[PDB]
Image (cartoon, rainbow over all chains, first blue to last red; front, side, top):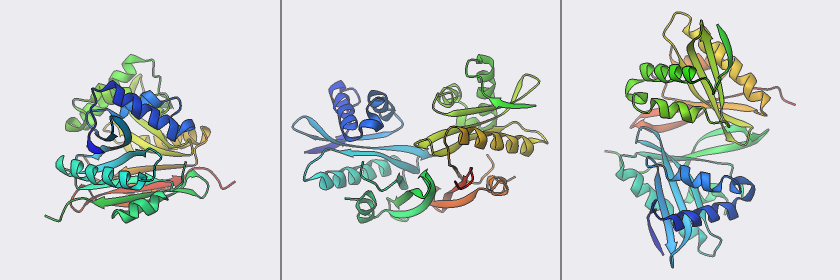
Length: 155
Length: 155
């Protein structure tokens, strides 16, 4: 497969991202599917696709939250398959390179660490470290964990 | 002055929020001023205005990030004046009530704690506690601090 910048002018690729979001998180994107995709296509954001045989099998994005130095990893969606983790890993590695090329220094993310491999385990193996916790985020005692990584060497 | 839900159908009130954002953070909203206001008017978000003599003197908003239980305080902008802190305080207190009424349990925020009273001091006195830190967020050693508060009693 190929990992590259998502072609925001390919309506079919956007339809597939839409279907991927809907099928992965029904009552989470089932209605705002197309709307979410448009948000993800915002020029300020980074958008990366994993394509195999002209089929979108994965997507990862990043949002510049603090200048162009601090970015939020969002979202990361990969099709169901036995190479899912490898797809995700390649998506993450490509994203870090993209982010760094736009002046990014650090990438953070928020996860409830639930399956809707545990997200925490996945990111921990990629070098991400817990930088914060929000209690009751998703409900009493149901926290959200924030993880981050400095994606470039100390100058 | 009066603190109440922002009338999203009042174009003059939106023009004033636009001017407030531009004048408070020139090279931060100087161009995306109107665009930022439209984002802030999104129906899912909470929008609160501080109005005095038909003049918008302050604004505070919240974004539902985790279901309807976890909300992000963003933004908080108050005009320059000697009652600025009191305006901000009343905005924050009204927001917490609004958030809680929509099923919210906790409110968090991110701050670089710089003046573009220190934001950290301001929120600390209102009951917000540090729940995380992102190093290099705004640049090397220039972190962003995340603060949060549970806005309703333990059931």
